[PDB]
Length: 273
Image (cartoon, rainbow, N blue to C red; front, side):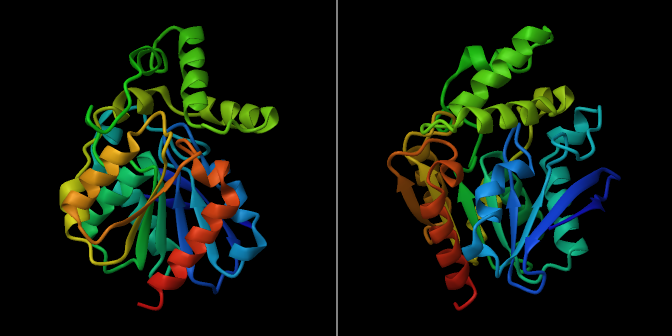
């Protein structure tokens, strides 16, 4: 495995990692809010995915990536799309498949809106944000308020509650503790701003020709699975979807064998269309 960095067009430095085969078909994994590259461990560790070029990175404001103080460095969805474009370019990734979890799905939509899909082979939205609208996002007024609060205990308690909402099948205690500390690395400036991040889902999704797969846990406690899927299919009727009946917001951790099977099958299909 390799570690390196990529500078985005606004100067933010992204922490990037690679695993698998450097000459294999690339897959770029894009994590969600309060995550980091650590979310993807069960994908990166699977021998059955090792013949792909497995690329992860930390989103701006997360993990070991740069964390600008200005809210306007986060509220413009294009900045996050440009981060992704910079990684696609720097890695010289040849028609990668994009895999975006939750906020990562919104990053893909903004990338599709700005750049189109001629540079990629397909995309998987994993419990992806489609739009940030009440008809598509589960109500949690206490948690959403607390996790951006100025009071330190309230803020940390809010993040811990949010991380619990990321699962139906809770992870073991040690994995939860790793992801909890990982979440505490996220920028408070980013957290307050990302609420207001623009998402060009209608433009990015409706124009896509590459294959798109939406994989959601049916019991997702953060993103409303069926309404998000339905909104996406309304925008692009060629989207395929799958519901994992007994997963919540993080099926790649909750049902990793099934997820890795679906992901490898999707990539194989996208590359032989």
